[PDB]
Image (cartoon, coloured by chain):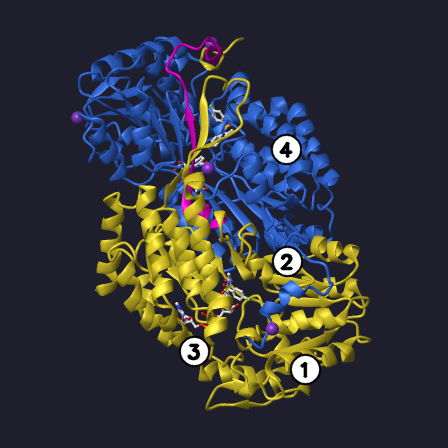
Chain colours: A blue, B yellow
Amino acid sequence: SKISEAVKRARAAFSSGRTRPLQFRIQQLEALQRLIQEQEQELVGALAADLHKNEWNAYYEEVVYVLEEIEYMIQKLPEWAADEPVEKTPQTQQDELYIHSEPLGVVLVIGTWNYPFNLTIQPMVGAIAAGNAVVLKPSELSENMASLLATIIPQYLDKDLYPVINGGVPETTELLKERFDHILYTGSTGVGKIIMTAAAKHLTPVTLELGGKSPCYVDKNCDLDVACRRIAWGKFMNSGQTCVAPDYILCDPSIQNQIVEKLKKSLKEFYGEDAKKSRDYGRIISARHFQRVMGLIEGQKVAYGGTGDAATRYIAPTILTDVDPQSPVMQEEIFGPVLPIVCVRSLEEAIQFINQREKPLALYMFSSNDKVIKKMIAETSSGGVAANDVIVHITLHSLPFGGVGNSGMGSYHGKKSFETFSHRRSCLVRPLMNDEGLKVRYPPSP
Amino acid sequence: SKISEAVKRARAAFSSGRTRPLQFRIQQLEALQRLIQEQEQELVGALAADLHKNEWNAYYEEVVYVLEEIEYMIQKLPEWAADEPVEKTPQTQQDELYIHSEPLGVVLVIGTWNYPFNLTIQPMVGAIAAGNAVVLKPSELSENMASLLATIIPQYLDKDLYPVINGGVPETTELLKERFDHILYTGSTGVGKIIMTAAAKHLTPVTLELGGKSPCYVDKNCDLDVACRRIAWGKFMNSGQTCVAPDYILCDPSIQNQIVEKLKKSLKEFYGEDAKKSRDYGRIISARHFQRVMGLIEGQKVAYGGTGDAATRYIAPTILTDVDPQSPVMQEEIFGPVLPIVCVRSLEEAIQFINQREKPLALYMFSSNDKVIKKMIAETSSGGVAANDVIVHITLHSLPFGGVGNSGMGSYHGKKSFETFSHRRSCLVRPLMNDEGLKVRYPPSPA
Ligand SMILES: NC(=O)c1ccc[n+]([C@@H]2O[C@H](COP(=O)([O-])OP(=O)(O)OC[C@H]3O[C@@H](n4cnc5c(N)ncnc54)[C@H](O)[C@@H]3O)[C@@H](O)[C@H]2O)c1
Ligand SMILES: NC(=O)c1ccc[n+]([C@@H]2O[C@H](COP(=O)([O-])OP(=O)(O)OC[C@H]3O[C@@H](n4cnc5c(N)ncnc54)[C@H](O)[C@@H]3O)[C@@H](O)[C@H]2O)c1
Ligand SMILES: Cc1nc2ccccc2n1S(=O)(=O)c1ccc(F)cc1
Ligand SMILES: Cc1nc2ccccc2n1S(=O)(=O)c1ccc(F)cc1
Ligand SMILES: [K+]
Ligand SMILES: [K+]
Ligand SMILES: [K+]
Ligand SMILES: [K+]
């Protein structure tokens, strides 16, 4: 079959030793760099057709971070790939003790649809840098990006080492029967379990980048002008279709009306009085998801927005108030421009609220008080944390990006991507000379 | 069930926050130091009854490294647990960026039988230091150690946080239905797949410490006296029942006879003429494994040993020559005192041989030529590597221990244990003051 052959050719090319020299990897990454520069309009086009992105946010909210990752990895590769000496003991002074980094082999990257370039290519960059063959499975939901990547990747990159495989569920099930040396999966908690089950059959290590509801706690005595502007930015970009979007707000009932009004002011600033007319406002990926997000608005108190167009898959920036935690909008990942506000009367109640639910990919807190920040961090568990801003904690090379519990396992970005797509091999090199100090270990015992 | 209640009590005790302060963790580790000191003779008795270990090798080939691990972690815990500052970027000048370490929750440790104290308690030490509740599932095959640990662990460690669950396959199957936040499993490649399949149902991360056949390449132009003494020591300790034992030898046919003779000399030095009489020589764990290893000797050219005793599960140190790589002794992990010699005509042939097989837990090479050492490392893959020795690489705090591919995933020992049993949480703390530099990111976008 097409899938079986593509994978075969990928392993055969890895087995030939082609990817081992650092210069080969760098040249593949520089080819990727040229692909992004030369196919920029095509990439914008794909994102515009899939998610209603424009040339600005297609670049500065997705593409640029791939480029920054490529530049960073090219520069750092010599340092990362070097044998790393580790601390010796008095008994191992004459020995070499070091960590040897080596490729895993054939890596499978399964992408998702909300950032269909970044979440296919940024994992790929790390895997290429680590010296792996990389099989790409882009999301079928983002049809235009999926089609484009299958076309343009083989034009710039090694055709055998880095194949693109497109398809739906059966094709993915078929792909998952193939033997890989690592699988990075970005997607749902439910399918994540299926991915790990398939990986178990070949003892394939997994990086699962999954979902959940990222809580956003707003402290009663903080600058709400700054806070709500930052929150509205993170929540409503890509029409709320961000894994690290502030899913819901936790706040004192005394500031709920103030929060509504400031989110309001920020949303008008960003997208005008009518967001349907903003070139900067996105659309829902599919009809299936449009219906889902609209269904979560039913039976709720709509403080802002609430209306949607099925033909264009537009959903107005919606703010819900006094939301019952047991209602549908607070029982699933929204992944849409619907921001529910849930009232809690203390920091302690907020911590308990977060702790009683599944561990989120991101946790957000807005507070002028640092003890509040540190207390919430120490008493909760989440993939990552950002205090007094949203989203940005995943844009920094020095901060590994990943989940915990239901939000996932493993992590990547920057050096972590190199590590994750490598095997770190402990090495002890000794002289083959008679050492009297070793005599104690040999039988007979004293 | 008793299994469900024990896991429930462990989660409840963790959810209380009891393990969070470092003093509490240190106190549990000190209790393990106390356990080892006060139960030394009982630990020896268990290992003697299970594996025919003696008071010396029970301590110096197992127990002492748990103690060293405990001493090391107690000292380093403040350093490890502290928030880790990371490198800033030009825009993140006024921000705090760090990595915050936190426990995962309830960790399950499934131990194996060959080093039944070390491979239950060393992983536990790491999981304790990282602030987890820890459920211990000792191997049923090492019966005496399993029983002892069920008795002595609650006598020293917190009873709710650190329960011991004994049982066979049915009990483990039920235990694997419980929800854990991490599982460290030490055992076979096949059962590793079963554990990972179970873990998938709860999205539980796994550290799998598995098996394979660790190759030992012996170069032509090296000191064979020194080499074979080191090899024989690694291969024949614990009656060959070591995951990182040099499973088989790859060498040029021109040095095969010399290797045989020098292995024989070393074995005579170690255990005498008749190893059955040596206090330092172990026994096979079970009747099933006795028959299995004896089966692997059949049809082979025996150059030394080759005999056994079913009643005592004794198998004489055995060397096999001119071994067909396709024969039974070369198609499975031996895990016994049978050392096959397989002939290769070059380093290149040896590299190809290793690469055709599944990735081993350890890879060994003996050579005076650094280029041979570096080429074999660069062109092969294995969990860990030692050049000009065996076993030792697993005893060092600064070298993480674990497999790759069929030999496993993840790693532990030293700092790596703390990291493996923690969630490393990326944290960005910004000031809540107006920043003009951030305004560029907000809509509306420029034309
Ligand atoms: N952590 C991250 O980095 C990150 C990034 C983006 C999105 N996400 C998460 O992804 C989720 C949304 O993305 P999504 O792609 O799951 O959307 P979705 O669930 O709408 O997409 C359905 C996808 O699942 C696949 N699928 C369905 N059944 C399958 C089976 N039996 N086997 C294999 N594949 C199967 C389909 O092929 C399809 O691609 C959100 O929960 C979000 O939090 C996480
Ligand atoms: N990497 C390491 O740290 C390390 C250390 C020691 C041993 N090992 C490996 O362990 C292997 C031998 O140890 P072993 O414990 O597998 O002994 P073994 O092969 O005798 O296996 C018996 C064990 O498997 C379990 N088992 C069997 N079927 C099962 C099922 N369906 N579900 C759950 N459990 C099941 C049994 O309960 C029993 O405990 C060797 O391959 C060795 O390399 C690895
Ligand atoms: C760098 C990065 N890591 C991500 C992880 C998940 C989703 C998008 C991600 N991105 S991203 O697409 O580049 C990105 C998305 C939004 C944003 F505001 C800034 C960056
Ligand atoms: C420290 C250590 N790491 C291990 C990993 C696997 C099996 C035994 C292990 N040990 S051990 O039992 O202490 C050990 C075993 C044999 C030996 F020679 C020295 C130490
Ligand atoms: K309501
Ligand atoms: K001695
Ligand atoms: K630290
Ligand atoms: K602006």
Q: In the image, which residues are magenta? A: B416-439
Task: Residue A206: give x, y in percent of width and height.
Answer: 49, 49
Task: Residue B187: give x, y in percent of width and height.
Answer: 47, 66
Identity of the amino acid at label 4?
Met
**Point 58% across, 79% down: residue:** B337
Residue B194 can be seen, yes or no: no
Q: Nearer the viewer, mark 4 or mark 2?
A: 2
**Point 44% across, 10% down: residue:** B435
Q: CA distance from mark 1 to mark 2?
A: 24 Å
Which residue is at the far front?
A446
Other-residue count near label 4 (Cα within 10 Å), few / some / many at <14 / 14–19 / ≥20: many
Q: Which mark is residue A73?
A: 4
Q: CA distance from mark 3 to mark 2?
A: 30 Å
Q: Chain of mark 4?
A: A
Write down the residue under mark 3. B48
Other-residue count near label 1 (Cα within 10 Å), few / some / many at <14 / 14–19 / ≥20: many
A27 or A289: nearer the viewer: A27
Q: Do badges 1 and 2 share one subunit?
A: yes
Say whether residue A146 is magenta: no
